[PDB]
Image (cartoon, coloured by chain):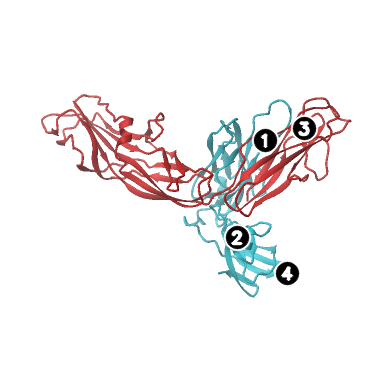
Chain colours: A red, B cyan
Amino acid sequence: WNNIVFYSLGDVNSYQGGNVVITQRPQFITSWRPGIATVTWNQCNGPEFADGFWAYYREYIAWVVFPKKVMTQNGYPLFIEVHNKGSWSEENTGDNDSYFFLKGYKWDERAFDAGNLCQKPGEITRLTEKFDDIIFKVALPADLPLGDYSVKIPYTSGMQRHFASYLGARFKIPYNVAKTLPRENEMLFLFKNIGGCRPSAQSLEIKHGDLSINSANNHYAAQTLSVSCDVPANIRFMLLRNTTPTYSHGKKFSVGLGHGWDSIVSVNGVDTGETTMRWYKAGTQNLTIGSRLYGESSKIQPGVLSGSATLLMILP
Amino acid sequence: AVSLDRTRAVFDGSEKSMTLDISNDNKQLPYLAQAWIENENQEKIITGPVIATPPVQRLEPGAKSMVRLSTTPDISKLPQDRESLFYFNLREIPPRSEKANVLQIALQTKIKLFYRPAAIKTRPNEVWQDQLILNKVSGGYRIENPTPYYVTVIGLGGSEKQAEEGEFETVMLSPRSEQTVKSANYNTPYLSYINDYGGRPVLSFICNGSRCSVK
């Protein structure tokens, strides 16, 4: 005979993530805590009660069925991630909706202790076993509104019990049914989104079609990057040199494109190679990177040009 | 097009390390995220009291990841009664481009890094650090800061609107320094900070002769 019982702790608490930028991921800690855990599900196929006459084997396992995603009252949907799980064993990648953290405490503990082997729904016991804290770090989309939040996140947490006749007891609740269990324990999460700016997420290539040998001497091309923003912001931009240029231009910024060809690279019309975009009010702003080519017959060479630069953003 | 999680990073002196999220927001291509630390002179420090690991990593298109700022016991040579300044950089390395004449550009964030000892460890609550003393002199104010902390003032004006909107060359005041900045005299002044968490507050002042304390 095999016999399974579960209790749900139903823990309540709140965690202040504090002030974060939209790109920043805030965090909360889901502590396991002893307390008075109520039975809510069981699968019984053995003796109802236990006595001194006959022995039986044990297996106790913990559970925390934490939801994979949540949506704010604002209607925007938050995403949760596991920063630090601990000695807990997460055991279900396949299912999307919830994480499945669990820990086997006992296994094959041959015990004679008399009492209730199948407490039916609504009965209670005082669980007094500790486990690790499970830490979570939350993901916020750029469109999240600025200000204070208070996301109430429900979850199940509790200790599965398995009393058994057979040696080497191995019975565990299915993941599907684990999801359906009462999410009695949930902890409010409070955090503040100050917001922040994020640049365009794209390839920065600037293309010139034809080598043209000597004829393409002062050839021009350029490309633009968006830089969206929620709040007021300064972003000191500085083009940096990777490939060292062949010729010298006084205060103009330059990059070697190879074969005795430079590119005088500019940003918002600046040969100097430094600018500054500023945000008084919110919204995006474009940033226009000029590449002007330059060579001279003395060291002009046939071949395919290519160089590079590093547009460095000094966020103060 | 990898980017960082925060504008500016504060290293707790009590703790041994800290994790900063990055994320390859380009979803068509994979990228390499070079990560490094620089001293207050903005030069690279390779064995330095703080170090960042890993120095390079492949981020698959769309993939988010971390970097680890951490300590070496030559941190004890730092001063413990005040913050020390570093900068944590991050440079994206693109896939070398398809063969055509092409200039390749590469984004790089360069945030501030504040080693803050445990002796001066801040309250969890945004602590004030509001003690500031704008002193009038020819050409404008001379801003005192006798706090043991780095403080970037981003604006100065007559009102909360002027400080927020009005043009001003940003100044970072080292702990225990006084520095002159150019500005028109204000009957009641307004200085705009950038706090640990990143948002830009506004302090308002009360000028009793040369000395102006906060309200």
Q: CA distance from mark 3 to mark 2?
A: 43 Å
* Residue type, label 3: Leu
* Residue type, label 2: Ser
Q: Are marks 3 and 1 in contact (CB under 8 Å)?
A: no
Residue drawn at x 69%, y 63% is B180
User: In the picture provided, is A195 more to the left or to the right than A50?
Assistant: right
* Residue type, label 4: Ser
User: In the picture provided, is B21 more to the left or to the right than A185?
Assistant: right
Q: CA distance from mark 1 to mark 4?
A: 47 Å
* Residue type, label 1: Leu
- x then y, percent, for residue A206: 72, 34
User: In the picture provided, is B53 more to the left or to the right than A9?
Assistant: right
Q: CA distance from mark 2 to mark 4?
A: 22 Å
- Chain ID of residue with mark 2: B
Task: Tell me the crowding category of disc 3: few under 14, some 14 to 19, or many 20 or more residues within 10 angstroms, Cα based.
Answer: many
Find disc 1 in the rendering and name its residue.
A204
Task: Tell me the crowding category of disc 2: few under 14, some 14 to 19, or many 20 or more residues within 10 angstroms, Cα based.
Answer: many
Whether residue A17 is visible: no
Q: Disc 3 vs disc 1: which is toward the camera?
A: 1
Q: Residue furthest bottom?
A: B209
Find disc 2 in the rendering and name its residue.
B192
Q: Is residue B155 above or below residue A34?
A: below
Residue drawn at x 54%, y 45% is B73
Disc 3 secondary structure class: loop
Task: Tell me the crowding category of disc 4: few under 14, some 14 to 19, or many 20 or more residues within 10 angstroms, Cα based.
Answer: few
Label number found at residue A257: 3
Find disc 4 in the rendering and name its residue.
B138
